[PDB]
Amino acid sequence: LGGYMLGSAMSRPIIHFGSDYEDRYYRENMHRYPNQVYYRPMDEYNNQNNFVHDCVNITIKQHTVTTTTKGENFTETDVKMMERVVEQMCITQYERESQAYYQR
């Protein structure tokens, strides 16, 4: 990892995709899927899009590299479903820190 941290735990979003089968498929198969995302503190770096692109590229990776040793099943369809959720949790998470910093 180096300097990444985890955020703070919450629910996961419910995300429709063009059929509620894909939403429900994901929601019934959350479990493995991350709930908090990994990202870094400012140190000048602050972004929305490039915190989120990072988080969707670090959280996902540190859920594939580990996965390659436990015989897991994450197809591209699973990775896409994961990224979709990780994005939204990350955007949501970034709003908790954004409001919390702006409120200080």
Image: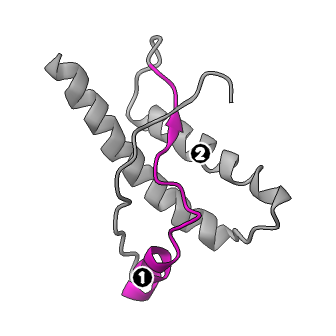
Describe residue 82's horizontal placement relative to residue 71 as left or right: left
Q: Are the two marked residues, 1 and 2, in contact with CB atoms closer than 8 angstroms?
A: no
Determine whether 17 is above or below 100 in the image. Answer: below
> Which residue in the protein does label 1 denote?
24
User: Front-most of 30 and 89?
Assistant: 30
**Residue 104 percent location from the top left of the image:** 17, 16
Quote the CA–CA distance across marks 1 and 2: 22 Å
Displayed quadrant of residue 15: bottom left
Nearer to the camera, 10 or 41: 10
Instruction: Looking at the picture, tell me which residue is in the foreground, 93 or 9.
Output: 9
Q: Is residue 39 magenta?
A: yes
Give the residue type at disc 1.
Arg
Q: Secondary structure at mark 1?
A: helix
Coordinates of residue 4 in the picture (x, y in percent): 58, 28
Above or below: residue 93 compared with residue 99: below
The three-letter code of the residue at mark 2 reads: Thr
Instruction: Check the image and report above or below for 79 versus 8.
Output: below
33 in magenta: yes
Q: Quadrant of residue 90?
A: top left
Residue lying at the far top in this picture: please name it: 43
Q: Is residue 60 left or right of residue 69?
A: left
Q: Residue at x 41, y 21 (%)?
A: 46
Quadrant of residue 20 in the image? Answer: bottom left
Of labels 1 and 2, earlier in sequence is: 1
**Residue that lies at the very extreme toward the left in this rendered image:** 103
Q: Residue at x 42, y 37 (%)?
A: 49
**Residue 31 place in picture, x, y as percent:** 53, 67
Q: How many marks?
A: 2
Q: Which residues are the magenta region?
A: 19-41
Q: What residue did someone put label 2 on?
A: 59
Q: Which mark is residue 77?
A: none
Residue at 35 percent of width and 51 percent of height: 10
